[PDB]
Length: 302
Length: 297
Ligand SMILES: O=C(Nc1cncc2ccccc12)[C@@H]1NCCc2ccc(Cl)cc21
Ligand SMILES: [Cl-]
Image (cartoon, rainbow over all chains, first blue to last red; front, side, top):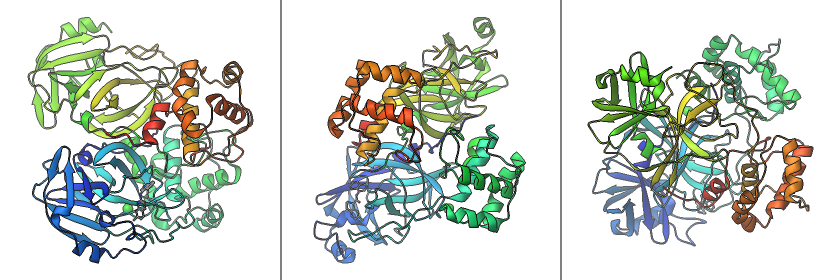
């Protein structure tokens, strides 16, 4: 019993964090095999941040301009290439702590753990979700660039995120490990605003099923709804549309609890209308949306 | 910017998790140097049940390697299995007993394999509101100070309300609990006041000021109100501990107490603080400073 926002154990990722210094800029790199991955904005100066030409700035750099530090060991950069918004520094040593890994690009609503780092040293680990507006509500200070988001399903680390920047609202933007940004963001100081954020509906339903599995049933009702009627109500509360894929995904939880997805949708509609009334669901007074259906099953069953 | 419930990086602890099997029971062990620590309920008159056990009855597995048990002893509610091999991944460590209100990270394990890491607090009623399934016994709570892991908790059981009970690494239970199937109930819980204030300072540091007011209060008047809402008494030590946050934000601790007093008597009014509609009490003043300054390990 119990339901916590749980991150993956960060050990496999900690053994990959390095510090990447280029000129006056220092941030984090991810050392996997003989390559160090980091945000390409590490090659940027003061006046080369509003409109940087990364191809032009990178051509002027030599291998010895990049200082990579793994613990108290300086690694030797023997090559450099750019892939989208990520810089790949070929090094003369393969990381002995390289875990079994994959680069995966996630979709909004997906969760992952973040290993926040400063100067190549891990400071903390927390659980996040890719918001529908493609930002992450992380916890990052200056120097956190290069910190990574990942999932550890089985013994394989799936890297899904690399931190690049903080938007004016305090939310964060970044890329997959191939350098493709999540959302309409670019790695420059130009005016960029996150779109209006919405609640990840399928995740709220997954969390309502977690509450039922843990013995919380007060919010259940005798009603059901059509998928269309639910979405018409949901949109009015800035909730993401629930698709037939989401209904299918929630099938296992519906089978385990005996509460049909559209039946749980009618509970969610009622909660949106009434609020909680001094009550909590799994120790929360708000509807939690950073637990996917897969997270709920893993945490409640194994 | 941002404020998250953040756990310590769990790597140093992951290299210590092993699986301990005794008879039909399988749980987790903590392998430090040549000793494996685990809950004694893996084997009631525990002295008598332990005397009937031989070293080969304990099957300890570190990854795909079976470790050989060369000795066994009991210290309070923890079993210590002496093994032939010292753990090469043994970090710099200490066994520390924490006080209610203090926070720590939990590395939840099943069959000696880490499955997740979360942050939690020792409740004033000595329970932890964890996330644990069958097989999680032996999972440990810890903090990291510089490069030293301070082990503070070992999971033993789940109480009927779904909350959890366990011991320090010397086998002394936190709270009035015993390691036996019997009627045991967690006492009435209270809110960790100093932690709520620390979290209000974290909200101010992140730009949330709506709850601030022009008012201040005496420590005595605050505690009279706090006692009424099942909040822990705020001591002069807590006020001193909150000093650095008070200096950084410009909001005196008793000034923040007047904000808390109003929040208790009047509620949030549809508003949130750091994305929460409840007052968060599982961040200590040190946690807030560590996260709002970026201390690394
Ligand atoms: O956002 C960046 N860094 C940070 C990242 N996270 C939390 C921060 C908090 C406080 C200050 C900086 C933070 C990075 N340096 C600032 C300008 C900038 C502009 C464009 C790009 Cl691509 C990156 C950057
Ligand atoms: Cl995905």
